[PDB]
Image (tube, rainbow, N blue to C red):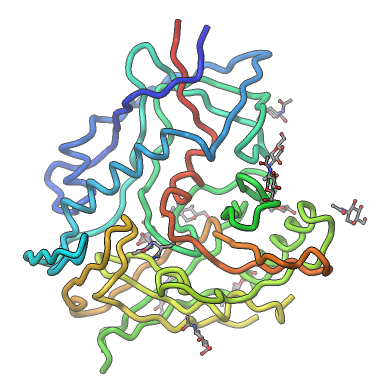
Length: 339
Ligand SMILES: O=C(NC[C@@]12CCC[C@@H]1CNC2)C(=O)Nc1ccc(Cl)c(F)c1
Ligand SMILES: *[C@@H]1O[C@H](CO)[C@@H](O)[C@H](O)[C@H]1NC(C)=O
Ligand SMILES: *[C@@H]1O[C@H](CO)[C@@H](O)[C@H](O)[C@H]1NC(C)=O
Ligand SMILES: *[C@@H]1O[C@H](CO)[C@@H](O)[C@H](O)[C@H]1NC(C)=O
Ligand SMILES: *[C@@H]1O[C@H](CO)[C@@H](O)[C@H](O)[C@H]1NC(C)=O
Ligand SMILES: *[C@@H]1O[C@H](CO)[C@@H](O)[C@H](O)[C@H]1NC(C)=O
Ligand SMILES: *[C@@H]1O[C@H](CO)[C@@H](O)[C@H](O)[C@H]1NC(C)=O
Ligand SMILES: *[C@@H]1O[C@H](CO)[C@@H](O)[C@H](O)[C@H]1NC(C)=O
Ligand SMILES: *[C@@H]1O[C@H](CO)[C@@H](O)[C@H](O)[C@H]1NC(C)=O
Ligand SMILES: *[C@@H]1O[C@H](CO)[C@@H](O)[C@H](O)[C@H]1NC(C)=O
Ligand SMILES: *[C@@H]1O[C@H](CO)[C@@H](O)[C@H](O)[C@H]1NC(C)=O
């Protein structure tokens, strides 16, 4: 027998000890080797309830990623608590690797295998495992990158859809590549992201149809963020140690519902910390071509309020709470204590 419970997890990975890449370094000191032959027991006729929005695994991963960034991505100047911290800010090697989360003895991880599981409620197909799949701690806003894809239909996740204050996570069942480059050769901070318009608009259309299922067939409208910090109004992410801020207005217009979509981007040195601890300044971009090709596997949306007396629902790209990023991958897991 077992029961819902919280415990201190540990991590496993395939990090390389000789690698200077910061994720590899962190995992080499903070994790253990993965199990080449992991066991998974499928529970028969066992119904378990899950709540992705109240899952301590999320807080723990958040804590790891904060620790990793605090140890490997120190800015030149930190502005937190009214105090000023000046440190050395050397360029680093940066590229997220898969991190596994595992339970100690006496505990096990329950995994929901229902094809269209939305993250909350009962689950029919449950299995037990010692470790989650390899999860890359990719930090971003608006768009979820290099994540896992839904297996069947596109899934809509939210602690409470009726509450517009609750973030919506869109889980795609098909990747859409985004190609971001800061050309070698001028404005060293100028950059751009390219995206196949035909693929994107087709996916966004599918997302529209899915949202209809959850909103009584009301008309679904996309719009760019109304306000807020740059980290939220724009698609922000880290590519090779550099912070990219991309204008996604071209992605979220309802006109295309086919050529290459070119999003204007800029590399910023001064950032609002996702750890929510003030601002940070980093050194200028490294020389040469700075390029990252990522899979868009999910979208973070916020719904406009005050539309109850209309046939429209308005959705704008959002984010800013990186815990939602971890939820998008940890939704199917929960920890239980064994007898
Ligand atoms: O600052 C952040 N969040 C906090 C706010 C989002 C919600 C309200 C908070 C007020 N300031 C913005 C943030 O995510 N920053 C941030 C920084 C770098 C990257 Cl790569 C990123 F993806 C996000
Ligand atoms: C349970 O999981 C299996 C395997 O993925 C799937 O075929 C089935 O549709 C799911 N639904 C049930 C019956 O629990
Ligand atoms: C990008 O997505 C494709 C599937 O669409 C996958 O094969 C590939 O491994 C992904 N790359 C990542 C996650 O870095
Ligand atoms: C993606 O999900 C949608 C429903 O949300 C479905 O219509 C479509 O067939 C799915 N595509 C793939 C690649 O499975
Ligand atoms: C997930 O499914 C449960 C019922 O199993 C339902 O109460 C909840 O509204 C669903 N979540 C979403 C976001 O649709
Ligand atoms: C969901 O949000 C709505 C709107 O704020 C609220 O009225 C309702 O009580 C919430 N539902 C739950 C389950 O708390
Ligand atoms: C990414 O886009 C750049 C645009 O300059 C292009 O040179 C490169 O071939 C693209 N890479 C992939 C994997 O499509
Ligand atoms: C754009 O996407 C379509 C599929 O929707 C694909 O067939 C085509 O090759 C893509 N165009 C380019 C320029 O690669
Ligand atoms: C949306 O409209 C279709 C029309 O075929 C209907 O079948 C379906 O029940 C409607 N869904 C909602 C959530 O209103
Ligand atoms: C994105 O680009 C559009 C078109 O140039 C512009 O109107 C809008 O203000 C930009 N968004 C942000 C957040 O700067
Ligand atoms: C996504 O994965 C690809 C392949 O490993 C990588 O090149 C790219 O930099 C990743 N994107 C981000 C934002 O980390």
